[PDB]
Image (cartoon, rainbow, N blue to C red; front, side):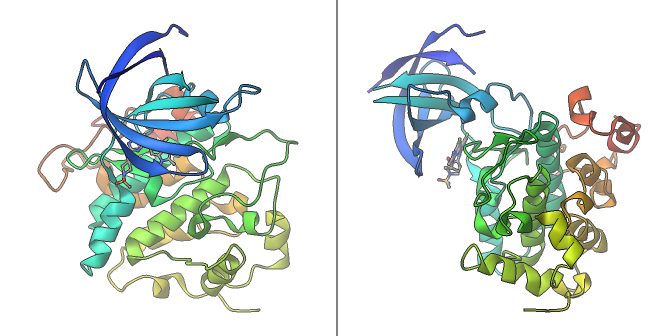
Length: 332
Ligand SMILES: Cc1nc2c(F)cc(-c3nc(N[C@@H]4CCN(S(C)(=O)=O)C[C@H]4O)ncc3F)cc2n1C(C)C
């Protein structure tokens, strides 16, 4: 059974696109996500079908049309169906950081630090890119970090919670997946910045080192109790910057004995109560935890070369251009 639609490439000029072998792979309040095979190339795609009101633009679509980056899933096409549905057609990526982490956790093992470095570095590159446009993802979690098993390339997906943040325009605070939710959001802040994604990235890093979520809250409010158990009660000034008294647990005692000190140091500079005290994504990319990735002899565990990690555009470096001397090593 072949379906033929008139799709606009993600130059607004539609073309006929045919696909087959459709199967449901995902769900949500937005609608359904399918996997399908394009007829000409045989390439696999993910098709996200969203119920769309004909009165007003789709925010996810407008954000996806502006993105062109190696570490973000590419919007190949979009089309309409049926009650109108918007359908986003993206290149299919079979694995995720969530599935990889779960496999290690069930086998009582930790993910090799080379993979933690490769995944986190590519996530920080995708965030430096989207943040350079004022766009905040607002749902950074391991389930939205797609991985190519053979190349170790990471791609950020699901821009359904994303938003261009404009100063003076309030934003919803009950946002982000709970375990990865920044403390200013739990305090009800509506004037938050892109640094909420950096808190989420720090939660993903800590989870990859620990083998389980660092802050496993059982409700939106208990999420703050879980955070407090580790970072201690925030001071009055920390609370002001964001929007059961306990002393902070020492960072070295949070992680396992053989955890690299550079991973702990990076984690401590991401999981800060004060949003402005957190590293920006470009600064996180320049951290000494990623030094091994800038070694000219670095290879993936399967013997292949690592993905292209140094092809930074001017747009990616725009927040701090002098960081290119650390980010692009002389051999590249
Ligand atoms: C809510 C949402 N919006 C999405 C979107 F815009 C694109 C994609 C997407 N997904 C994939 N692959 C995923 C590999 C993992 N599997 S699983 C958990 O093993 O069944 C789900 C599958 O959707 N590939 C490309 C995409 F753009 C996935 C999306 N999702 C969920 C399913 C993560």
